[PDB]
Image (cartoon, coloured by chain):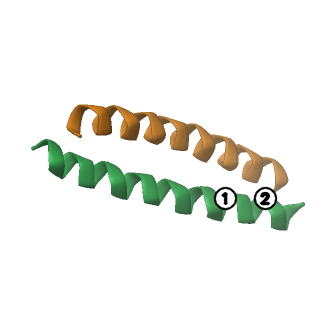
Chain colours: A green, B orange
Amino acid sequence: RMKQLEDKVEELLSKNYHLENEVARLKKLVG
Amino acid sequence: RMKQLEDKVEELLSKNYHLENEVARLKKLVG
């Protein structure tokens, strides 16, 4: 169902943005 | 539509794993 799939997309995007935030913070640590 | 949404989840999923790996590599290295 469409709804469940839409939601899964929204959720994955949201986890992805969280992980990209971490990478940038860790990047800042590196240099 | 259904099949494009499935594909997007698959794509986000793949991306998420790559970011996790990346986050794991940078942490090790950094802290």
> Tag 1: Cα neighbours inside 10 Å, few (<14), some, or many (≥20)?
many
Q: Where's residue A26, x and y in %?
A: 25, 48
Given the current orientation, which residue lies at the most extreme left position? A31
Up/down of A12 relative to B29, above or below: below
Residue at the spot x=67%, y=41% of the render? B10
Give the residue drawn at x 48%, y 35%: B18
Q: Amino acid at mark 2?
A: Leu
Q: Is residue B3 left or right of residue A19?
A: right
Q: How many marks?
A: 2
* Residue B6 in the image, given as x and y percentages of width and height: 76, 47
With respect to residue B29, does A29 lie above or below? below
| Percent coordinates x, y for residue A12 in the rendering | 61, 56
Q: Which residue is mark 1?
A: A9
Quadrant of image for the C terminus of chain A: top left
**Left or right: A2, with B22 as reference point:** right
The structure residue drawn at horizontal position 68% and vertical position 48%, both measured from the top left corner, is B9
Question: Amino acid under label 1?
Answer: Val
Label at residue A5: 2
Do tag 2 and tag 1 residues touch (Cβ < 8 Å)?
yes
